[PDB]
Length: 31
Length: 32
Length: 31
Length: 32
Image: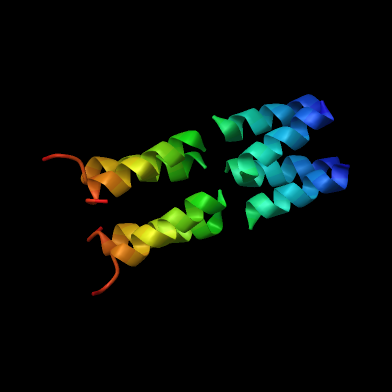
């Protein structure tokens, strides 16, 4: 069950995309 | 406790919608 | 230590704001 | 396992930056 949990944490980790998307949006907005 | 944990994680996972909404905004603002 | 963990999960929960902000941005963008 | 867990959670928490970046975008796009 600890494993299920850690599996859910890796699914949550699969956030950096969101960060990347945001950086890209700011730039498309003219910074 | 551990079922509160698994449930809080399912509540958090239930984020990809956010990523996809951002993918849309980025697409909308992209070069015409 | 289970408590520490559940505390971190409530901190993560404190995401709906992000959703709200996004809905507001789409609307400000002219939908 | 449990330290991998606590560490993955600290890696996730390390989100508020995202909220605040969105608060900025919303502020920028707000009525002049």
